[PDB]
Amino acid sequence: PIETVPVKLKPGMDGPKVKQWPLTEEKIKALVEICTEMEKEGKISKIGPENPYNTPVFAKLVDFRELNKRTQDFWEVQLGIPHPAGLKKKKSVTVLDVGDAYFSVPLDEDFRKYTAFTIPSINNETPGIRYQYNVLPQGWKGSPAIFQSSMTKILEPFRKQNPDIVIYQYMDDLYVGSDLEIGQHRTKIEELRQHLLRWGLYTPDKKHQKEPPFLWMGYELHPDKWTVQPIVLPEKDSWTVNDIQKLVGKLNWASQIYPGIKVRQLCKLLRGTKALTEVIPLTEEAELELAENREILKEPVHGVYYDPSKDLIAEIQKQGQGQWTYQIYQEPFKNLKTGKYARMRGAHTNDVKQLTEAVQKITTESIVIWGKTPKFKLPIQKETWETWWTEYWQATWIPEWEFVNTPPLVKLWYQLEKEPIVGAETFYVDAGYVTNRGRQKVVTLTDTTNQKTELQAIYLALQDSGLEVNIVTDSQYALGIIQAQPDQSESELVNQIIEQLIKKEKVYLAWVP
Amino acid sequence: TVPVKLKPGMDGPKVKQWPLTEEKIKALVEICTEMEKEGKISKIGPENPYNTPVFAIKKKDSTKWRKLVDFRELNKRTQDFPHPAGLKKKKSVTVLDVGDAYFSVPLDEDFRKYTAFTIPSINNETPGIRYQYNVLPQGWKGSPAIFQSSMTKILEPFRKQNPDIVIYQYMDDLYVGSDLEIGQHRTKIEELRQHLLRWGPPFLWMGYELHPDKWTVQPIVLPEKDSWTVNDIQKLVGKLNWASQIYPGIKVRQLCKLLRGTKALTEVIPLTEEAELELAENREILKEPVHGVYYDPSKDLIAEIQKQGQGQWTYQIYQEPFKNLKTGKYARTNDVKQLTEAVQKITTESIVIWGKTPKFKLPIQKETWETWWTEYWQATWIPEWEFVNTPPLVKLWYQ
Ligand SMILES: Cc1ccnc2c1NC(=O)c1cccnc1N2C1CC1
C-alpha cells in the first residue's frame, strides 16, 4: 500500500492515560455499530487490555488534544500557498475531492498503541471494548502532514508519465489542469482517479465533480482568467466602527487586482473612536471615496495568468502623499496582478526612499510568485535617483528600470549645500539663535520635548533668514533628520521646516559639539 | 562513523527557507539530484521537522553553481570539539576549497536529521523537495573536526617536504601561505593540488593570493590645508573631540579659541602659533593605532561598515568599542555587490589573522540584502550579521 511514517511521542513522555466520559446507552449503541463497521475494514482493531493508554470518545469524535500535546512536531503542513497570478493558463482544470483521505493511510505500527480508546459497556461487569487505530485518525497532529506527504509520493509517478498534466495538492482537494482537448483531458482525469484508486483513494466521478470557475481562498479561478470572488459594497446610512473596519478590510483585498481603490478617507473615520459599535457619520470626502470605490467595483476586472515565455513588467505610480500603486504585467494593461504600498519606514522619508522601498517589496513578491524579478517602469530619472543614492548613508540597489514620464514624477524638493555659503548670514542655534550680523531671538516653547526644542530653533532660523543661510547646530538629532532630506513627516514641525527648506535657494547645515 | 551531538538540552534547527529565484532553484535541483544518486543526501519524510536554508552561488571564472547551506544556526548548537600567527606575515596566501573532501566520510546516523534542508518551489505550486545529509556536509562546523585526522595524514608529507609553507584550514577552506616569489608560489600551489589528488581541486578567490604582508591600519586623518575657514575649524574640533575619546592626549583648547565669537562660517582664520603646535601634536598622535588593544580570543569579533561614496567604504574590526583591532578601506557595479565583496574580503582577513569570522553590522535593509547577496557571494562560509542605521557623524569621522 503506502509506506509508514515513523512517529514518536515527545521525549520523556508517555502516551495519554485519560478516562472515558460516561456515555449514553443510545450513544454507546451508535459507537459500536461505527466501530464494528470500522474493524471489519481494518481501520481499527480490538486490543488486549495490556494497553494502559486511553483517549476519550464521543458521538464518532475522538478527542486527541492530549495525544497531540504529547506527539512529536512534524514538518509544517506548509502554509505557503499559490497566488493566482503565478499560474499558467490551462484549457481544462478538474477539482478532485478526496474522501476518507486520512483513513486511507496507515499509521506507524509502533504508534497505534497510543491511539487507544474505549467504548463503555451497558451492563456493569460486562464488556468495555478497547481498540486502537491502524490508520490516520482525524484530529490527530500528524495526519495532515503524513497524508500530504504520502499523497505527494503517489502522484509523483503518474506525474512523470504525464509531464503535461499539472497537479496542485491542497488539503483534501486536488486541482488538475491540462492543455488537452476536453476529451483527452477528461480521459486522463479518470486515468488519475484510477491511479488513486489502486491505493483505494476515492475521488468523485465527473457527474458530481465541481465545475469552474473555482472559488478558492477568496478568488474565482477559471483556467484562463482570474479575479477575487466579487464584492458587494453596502448601502447603509449608519456606519459602526466595526462596519468600517470590515469594509476597509474587504477594500484592501481588492487592491491586488482592482486598480484605484483608496481608503485613506474611510480609514480616517476611525480616529479616536471609543467602541466597536460606535456610529461615525461619513464625511464629504469619505462618501466620495466610498462611491468612487463602489463604482470601480461595479465593473468586474479579471486578471490574466502567467506566460513564462514573456517578460514581466512592473510599473509604479504615486497615488497620494505616502501612497503608491503598481501593476505587474507581460502585455500592456494585461495585468497579472496589481497592488498598493503605503508602508512608511521611519518617521520621515522622501519619495525617493519610499519609491525605492516600494520596489523591494515588489521585487520580493515576484521572486515568490514567478521566481524572477520584473523590469520596472518608474516615474523618476536616473539623475534624481543616482543623486540621492550616491549620497545616502545606507547601501541600496534597484534592478533594471526604465524611466517613464508619467506624472507626478518623483524629485528632490531641495538639497543642502555641500559647503558653507559665502556671504550668507550665519545663525548659531542651541530655543533661540544668534547670527554673525548681531541678530537674535530667544523664543518661548511650552510642552516641548528636548528633541523637539532643537528643531524649533532651526525652524526659527529658517524663518527669519533670507534665501541663503548657513546654520550651525549642536543637535546631531536634527542634523540627521534634515540631512536625510525628508519631504514628508509624521511631525508637523518638520514639515514646516521642510517647507522652509524648499523655499530657500541654498542652505547649509553644520554641526558642532 | 563518529558520534556527534548537539550542545546539552538543545534541539535541532527549524529555520524558514528564504524564497528563491527559479534560476537558483533549478541549479539546486540539478545538483541535489546527483548528490542523491551518489547517496550523499537522502529525501526525508514529514516526521523530520528540522530545517536549514539552502542557496546556490556561482563559482568565479568557472561555469558551475555551488550549493551553499546556511548551517549557521546548527553550528551554534553543535557540541564544541589552533592558529598560525605566522600566516598573517606570510607574503602570499592562496585559498583552496577542500569542500568535496568531506563527502567520502559518512555522518553519524543519529545526527543526520539535523541537516534537513529544503528546496522550494515557485509560488508554492509543489510541496518542495526535502533532504538530509548522509555524509559530512560542507559548511558544518563538525565536518572539519571530524575530518581533521584524515587531513593531517595526507598533509604531513608536504608539511615536512615543504615546511617553508604554512597551511591553515578553516571550514571548507585551506589557506596556504609562503614568502616565495608569486611565480614560485603558483607552482608549489598547483603541486599540492595533485598531491591531494594522489590521496584524494579549486581555488577560491580567482586563483589569487592574498598579500596579508601588505595589510595596514587606516589611521584617522586630518585635512591638511592652505587657509582655514571657521567651518573648517569647526569640523576639525568636532573630529578631534570624537577622536579624543580614543587618544586622550589630544587637546583642542587652542583650536576652540580661534572659534570664539559668532563669526561667519566662511571667514578665513589664520591660525596662531599655539594652535599650529597643538594641531601638529594631535596630528602626530593620530599617526598610529592607539597603544594597548589586544585580541581576546574569548570575545566576539565585530565588524562595522560605513558607506563613504563613489564606491568607497570603511570598516573597522574590534571587540570593544573604540578599541579597534583593525581598520580598512574598500573601493569597487552597485552598492550591494560592493557590500558583499567587502564582507567576504573582511571575513577572509579575520580568518587569516585571528582564525575566526566577525559579526558584521550592515548599512542596508534586510529585505534588500536577503534579496541580492546570494548573487555576488562566492565564499563557502557565512558570517553572522545584523542590520543597522549608520550615524552621519561616524561616516564623517572616517576616510
Ligand atoms: C487552486 C489552484 C492552485 C494551483 N494551481 C491551480 C489551481 N486551480 C485552478 O483552477 C487553476 C487555474 C488556472 C491554471 N492552473 C490552475 N491550477 C493548476 C493545477 C492546474
Image: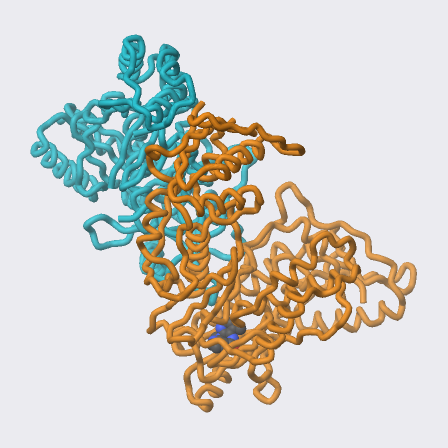
Chain colours: A orange, B cyan
Q: Residue furthest front?
A: A438
Q: Position of residue B59 (x, y in %)?
A: 25, 49
Q: Residue furthest right?
A: A124
Could you say which is closer to the camera, residue B352 or residue A455? Answer: A455
* Residue A152 versus residue B182 in the image, above or below: below
Q: Position of residue A487 (x, y in %)?
A: 47, 48
Q: Residue at x 79, y 73 (%)?
A: A33
Q: Position of residue A120 (x, y in %)?
A: 84, 61
Q: Quadrant of the C terminus of chain A?
A: top left
Could you say which is closer to the camera, residue A459 or residue B291? Answer: A459
Q: Is residue B314 left or right of residue A125?
A: left
Q: Is residue A442 left or right of residue A507?
A: right
Could you say which is closer to the camera, residue B379 or residue B133? Answer: B379
* Residue A3 versus residue B382 in the image, above or below: below
Q: Position of residue A203 (x, y in %)?
A: 58, 79
Using the rendered view, name the quadrant where residue A27 is placed: bottom right
Q: Is residue A242 left or right of residue B158?
A: right
Q: Residue furthest bottom?
A: A183
Q: Is residue A185 visible?
A: yes
Q: Residue at x 75, y 73 (%)?
A: A236
Q: Is residue A199 visible?
A: no
Count of marks placed on residues: 0
Could you say which is closer to the camera, residue B217 or residue B161? Answer: B217
Using the rendered view, name the quadrant where residue B143 is placed: top left
